[PDB]
Image (cartoon, rainbow, N blue to C red; front, side, top):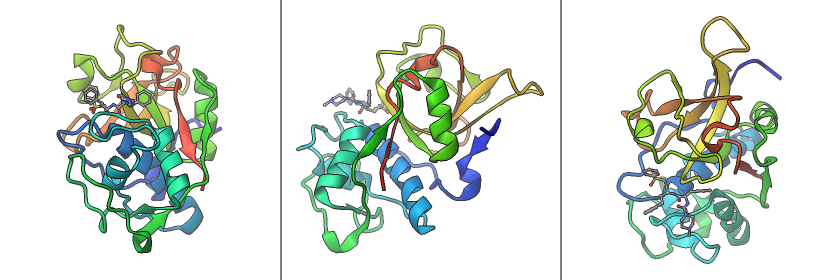
Length: 221
Ligand SMILES: *[C@H](CS(=O)(=O)c1ccccc1)[C@H](CCc1ccccc1)NC(=O)[C@H](Cc1ccccc1)NC(=O)N1CCN(C)CC1
């Protein structure tokens, strides 16, 4: 595998979005992964509708602004037979009634693939050969809220108790040593003003730091 990967450089990633005052992180992680996979198959990067996921995936177990799972979002897309674009189904950061319109569907999946739980080597393989991967992490510490640059490392992070869904768009390392200061390049959904232009580097190969590889998955297009 390459020593460094950054799918943003290949056009697989849309601009950083902002979930605002709604616990829809899972929806942004899901659309991010689907945007990358749809790009692989069509060569077109189209911003997808998180609102569509928020309003419509309750039957699959999601609770809109009150939390959800990327896996169940992918299941919704499969069962629903499609997902609308952001332009046609705008984000309003509140739970509303499903308004999915088939004519505006621009993405689909037939299910999803789960990365071996807790295996950072497996996650690395997926990121390198598949594209952006949806992941869950423990981002509940104040250190994460205040992240600005460098490699994020929180001694109190849990690899089991996760509370935030984000997107791994690559990996690499700082300094000159390819085997040191390694990190996962993560796209957050708190706007471009947060962290490093909306992104955060999470310590990689540091015993599955913050559970980055505990619940990773990607939609099958
Ligand atoms: C997104 C995380 S966030 O809101 O940006 C946030 C903010 C500050 C610190 C950490 C995280 C949401 C928030 C959900 C929430 C809303 C309101 C009150 C409490 C919580 N979190 C999720 O949706 C997580 C994502 C996830 C995916 C996979 C594995 C582990 C976590 N899921 C979630 O919280 N769920 C799952 C579904 N269930 C019905 C409700 C709770």
